[PDB]
Image 1 (spheres, rainbow over the protein chains, first blue to last red):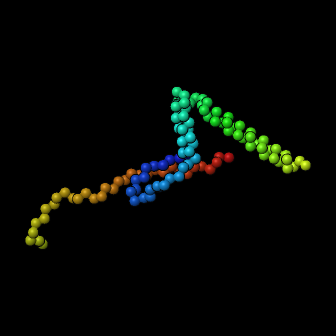
Image 2: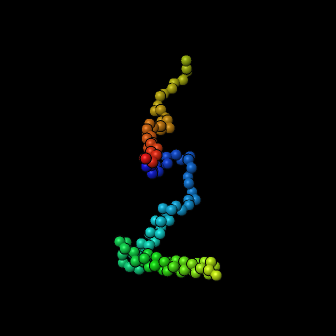
Image 3: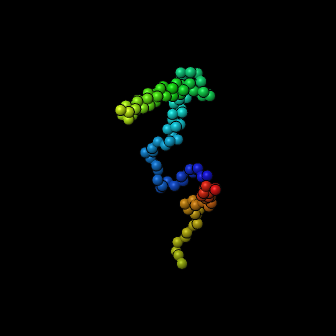
Length: 81
Length: 33
């Protein structure tokens, strides 16, 4: 339900400096960064499909396959005689 | 009882108060089950 943040009308109140980074903020930053990257490498900003994110995901999936096979053969060496 | 005259000019405006009724959105209802 409630989501708001009215304007503070008190001059003697508290002002919240030194903000952190929210999950929302970091997601928005990652999005705008992927959008700039798309607009630079390609000439798309409509972002209907992002092949760059797919490529990065592909390389990281390769890395995950790597580390998974590694730990798998490791525990295989240990458990088996 | 005075031997001197006083003249009534515009009253110095007080600090401006307003009657803006502040409305508060009710608490969120608990998860409807």
